[PDB]
Amino acid sequence: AAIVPTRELENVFLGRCKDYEITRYLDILPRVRSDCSALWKDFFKAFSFKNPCDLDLGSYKDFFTSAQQQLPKNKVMFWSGVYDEAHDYANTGRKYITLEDTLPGYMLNSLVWCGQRANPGFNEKVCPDFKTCPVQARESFWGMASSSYAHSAEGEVTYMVDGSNPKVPAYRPDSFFGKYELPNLTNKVTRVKVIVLHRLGEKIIEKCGAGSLLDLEKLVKAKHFAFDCVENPRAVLFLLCSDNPNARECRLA
Amino acid sequence: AIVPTRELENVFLGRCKDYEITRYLDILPRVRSDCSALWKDFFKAFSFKNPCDLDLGSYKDFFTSAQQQLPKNKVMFWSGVYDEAHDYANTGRKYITLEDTLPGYMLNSLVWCGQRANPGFNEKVCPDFKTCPVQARESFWGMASSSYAHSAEGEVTYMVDGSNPKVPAYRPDSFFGKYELPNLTNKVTRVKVIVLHRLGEKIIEKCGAGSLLDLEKLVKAKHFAFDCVENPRAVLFLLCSDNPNARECRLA
Ligand SMILES: NC(=O)c1ccc[n+]([C@@H]2O[C@H](COP(=O)(O)OP(=O)(O)OC[C@H]3O[C@@H](n4cnc5c(=O)[nH]c(N)nc54)[C@H](O)[C@@H]3O)[C@@H](O)[C@H]2O)c1
Ligand SMILES: Nc1nc2c(c(=O)[nH]1)N1CN2[C@@H]2O[C@H](COP(=O)(O)OP(=O)(O)OC[C@H]3O[C@@H]1[C@H](O)[C@@H]3O)[C@@H](O)[C@H]2O
Image (tube, rainbow over all chains, first blue to last red; front, side):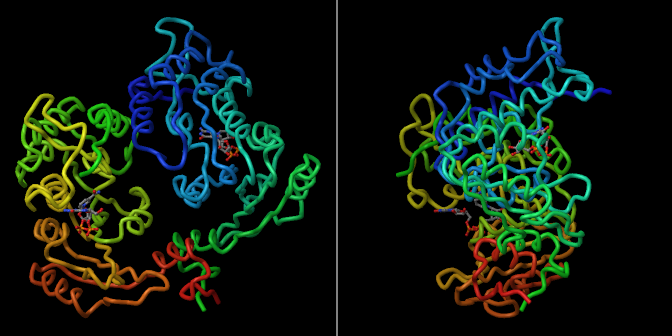
């Protein structure tokens, strides 16, 4: 019913922020104008002195306005259900960008924090489990993060999905992609390129042009973008094969 | 002459704090010293001295403060193959590299040097990696390698470039040759060499020949077991991911 928050949240935030500013993605993403301390103030204002369950999509809006970078054309990737594979393939910004390579994504990835009403306005020892909050509160931070990131995409965007999960459709309207990313693609986007990941040794569940992927195809087209879809394209298959080289799908000529 | 990192202390302390609270928590222990104490040891090694006035001892206190116990069988060394080895080690999930440990993570890619005048480090320019004598040029990374190799236990892995016509896969004067191999202790049981044959490039070096034979001789003389493989499938597949039309990557 509870989760342990990250210790020294301000120090971690500011330390990640300074590391990023001087050393990370230097030739891949631009620097943000606001200094780390200003970004901290915006971040801490969004959630402090508020019950976690009262947050909503607007809570972190000003922080994301300050933190948002212009993103390289054609390079933005979204992912659903395949965090490791999508990040491994995107290769720390070198092939695609993910939210986690952007400043706000990088500063807060993996961290846990919570406001409270009593002083000092946040809790550094215990946080309620967020499943108890309404969905707009639970999704307050990462939901706005995704919206702001998607809204900055231009050119082709790529969406990597799990095609091997019989319980979770490749495309779902209520996922972060469906709820915060796709609806925020602007007319600067030209094409949605879907990569369907079929895990090695698992029954194939979803296929391009069928089920939820056909629903997605229709929606992308109704939003006036080009669309393509590939299953385990060679480059991704080789990546899966590196972690399971003796899988039947990885046999050499 | 090369460009020093801006805000060196802010970056060191920011990476130090990030690492302390959030990085490698399930694979490497925390160190006892706080980030401000580690800064103090690091800074005193080079500060208020001419930028070449260093030797292997200069960062002794920093490295002893920063050294972590390392996961048995998980240590990797590398020469000439930065991206491939780091990609394969996969930020500590499969192997550890020096760059995943606290001191390697903090200083990786940074540039700094001392000067005599206040503030005791040069924020404008640092010497090219060739103007200082060898024991000074290798002072920080040499001792990082020494300390790291000395903490290795069980099987260790070494990835080398077998496709470089100018530079042997193994050299006694590389960091591995000079600082790592000689610091492997009796807790090490086996040196496992992985030879990278870059895709589409001529093979220069192979297991059981050339400098790999020299290495095998030395490893055995230390009573460690030895094996060597060229482009083992897991590594080949990683290479292929970035170049899937290469002839080495044709599938059944
Ligand atoms: N992260 C690092 O900067 C680093 C630097 C030096 C040494 N390591 C460690 O020694 C082993 C790799 O050095 P070594 O065996 O000499 O391999 P390389 O031949 O690839 O050289 C390693 C780094 O050394 C850099 N390099 C570049 N120029 C110089 C130089 O003039 N003098 C000098 N001593 N090193 C230089 C080069 O860009 C490489 O990134 C490895 O197992 C790590 O545990 C890591
Ligand atoms: N804690 C984090 N959460 C999230 C990041 C993130 O970096 N960290 N997220 C999302 N997110 C939240 O974590 C899950 C993963 O859902 P999952 O079902 O795997 O995929 P979604 O489409 O819901 O979310 C992935 C989407 O938003 C970023 C990243 O840029 C991807 O393109 C999702 O349901 C949200 O509740």
